[PDB]
Length: 51
Length: 51
View 1 (cartoon, rainbow over the protein chains, first blue to last red):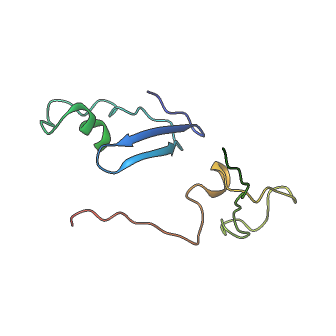
View 2 (cartoon, rainbow over the protein chains, first blue to last red):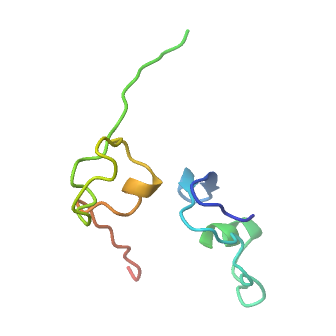
């Protein structure tokens, strides 16, 4: 999901709760081209929250 | 049954403190992307990682 400046996004963290985030600089949320293979840490949701 | 209330908030004058003059003589004193996002001088926040 591609961020756009001035917009508002919302998310819920598995360990701290829900929160609303306003993007300030356009960026790709996922990792750009990262968060695969080398992680070997946890579930899909826990990977998104870390990023 | 429902509840309703109106509060409103506002930035402080000289908050940015990097410019010597207001933009348009009369300007909104309410926080926004172009006036309050990470530009205030009254507050600094630093993450702590390692503990």
